[PDB]
Length: 145
Image (cartoon, rainbow, N blue to C red; front, side, top):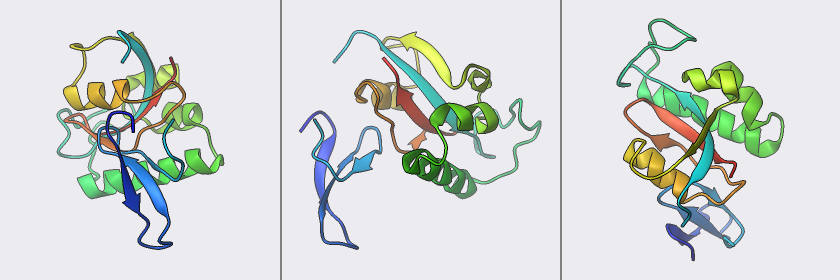
């Protein structure tokens, strides 16, 4: 399995699924290193975020668990198709890159926070991560290139 993927057992169904411990993505299908990848991300800060402020809200008061619920809900709406990633990041991302539909443009290793970097280069083009915890908050990373 590609870097970070591992088999696990569904404790509801008993059916086998795959999770990645780098990106926090889990899926049912069996899954399938570039100098540069291109990502968008959706950020949801919390009161233990490095800077608990955003264009959305001068004083971010939600907790870290509440930040996770929101992220999980967004992950659910993206993955159901009831919303797409660009729409949610524009409305709800605590990162001012929301003004560019999440897009951060392309980067290489050594520029970002290491957990974000790791999740990003362990995404395949067109893949979305799970919640990705950094000091800014919790991320949904989409790798677009």
